Image (cartoon, rainbow over all chains, first blue to last red; front, side, top):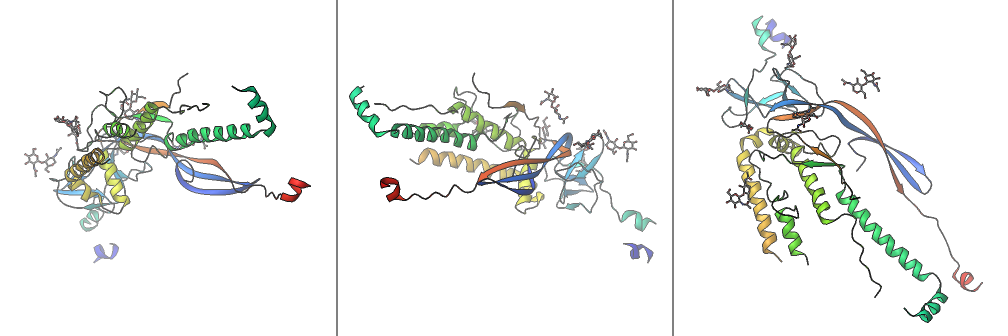
Length: 7
Length: 106
Length: 170
Length: 50
Ligand SMILES: *[C@@H]1O[C@H](CO)[C@@H](O[C@@H]2O[C@H](CO)[C@@H](O)[C@H](O)[C@H]2NC(C)=O)[C@H](O)[C@H]1NC(C)=O
Ligand SMILES: *[C@@H]1O[C@H](CO)[C@@H](O[C@@H]2O[C@H](CO)[C@@H](O)[C@H](O)[C@H]2NC(C)=O)[C@H](O)[C@H]1NC(C)=O
Ligand SMILES: *[C@@H]1O[C@H](CO)[C@@H](O[C@@H]2O[C@H](CO)[C@@H](O)[C@H](O)[C@H]2NC(C)=O)[C@H](O)[C@H]1NC(C)=O
Ligand SMILES: *[C@@H]1O[C@H](CO)[C@@H](O[C@@H]2O[C@H](CO)[C@@H](O)[C@H](O)[C@H]2NC(C)=O)[C@H](O)[C@H]1NC(C)=O
Ligand SMILES: *[C@@H]1O[C@H](CO)[C@@H](O[C@@H]2O[C@H](CO)[C@@H](O)[C@H](O)[C@H]2NC(C)=O)[C@H](O)[C@H]1NC(C)=O
Ligand SMILES: *[C@@H]1O[C@H](CO)[C@@H](O)[C@H](O)[C@H]1NC(C)=O
């Protein structure tokens, strides 16, 4: 989930 | 078959014209009452435990493994959704936490 | 009662002692077998007075309070369907105590599932226990919960068919 | 006396209550099983007749 909310 | 209780392991020992098995087993102890429900009704959906059981200590609902008390927050990672709340007898209303929910908020 | 016959029998030695020892060993072996089969619990479990098991009916297998023998109707039918130096030793466990042992086992497996066989008896609702058994054979809990009335009805129908088959087959 | 089968234990059953263990005991038990007997040979001629 960490790359998802970053983008 | 391998001792009284849930069998963990065994150790063999020789004896005169015989064998002695030392059965190491797991016995539950210090049990505690909890209020239980078959399913959790949330947002018109029925939630069932993936591997555990829903327990309540009186005010709050948790999910734990069946053979040991380890209360955890009821989330979508340890539960699964099947059907609505109209079918399961004894389903109760409780919130279901979403781990992804704080992520998109920030 | 012939003394001369016993005097002639003493010439053959300890054959009678051997036969009595073998019969005594068989007689204690039967009691040991009954202890091994039925006396596997040291706690006498009892069913609750309210038979709220989520639709499951156990009246055909639980003991009947109206009967003086304290047997189940199935067990009563089973007991009805089975008909010079010799002595018959009574068994160590009488029939009412064996029925009490079966009643304790039934109460343990109904009210506690398999928990009483591994330690202290942990209470659990019977539909939840059935769901656990469903998970043991790899079927999800939701299937059990959605069709709980159908499963209870099928179980009661099967138990009634078992009683009818036992009553109808010599 | 008339033998008591066991201590009475009325399980507190209800349709919505469960008992969950909070602790455990590592229990070691013994099981003794015979494996073999003494291997005895009897000379039938020497036993009966010397
Ligand atoms: C769970 O609740 C039941 C119901 O109150 C408890 O059973 C009672 O226990 C007390 C204390 O030993 C007895 O005096 C009562 O007779 C019991 N009632 C019944 C209906 O059995 C039980 O002890 C509780 N379990 C725990 C671990 O606290
Ligand atoms: C059931 O367990 C939960 C989890 O510990 C309890 O919730 C906490 O209770 C303490 C008691 O003062 C509070 O200080 C905490 O703030 C509570 N946590 C949360 C997240 O609210 C709950 O009280 C327990 N209920 C009962 C009846 O024992
Ligand atoms: C759990 O929540 C549902 C709705 O989220 C409740 O169902 C409502 O019950 C009231 C009164 O019985 C009805 O007037 C509504 O029409 C119902 N709504 C729906 C969508 O079914 C239910 O009563 C709640 N259960 C508990 C125990 O509070
Ligand atoms: C469980 O099954 C028994 C019998 O299988 C039911 O007892 C019957 O109840 C009806 C209506 O009350 C009577 O007309 C019959 O004579 C009863 N039969 C016997 C053998 O007693 C019982 O009602 C069922 N349900 C429960 C909750 O026990
Ligand atoms: C679970 O049971 C064990 C005993 O089998 C508990 O360990 C004891 O804890 C007390 C106080 O915490 C000590 O005085 C004893 O010396 C401990 N015994 C041993 C053998 O270490 C343990 O605390 C229990 N845990 C819970 C959560 O109840
Ligand atoms: C459990 O029994 C009580 C009777 O006091 C009843 O009100 C309740 O609806 C029952 N719940 C279920 C799930 O059968």
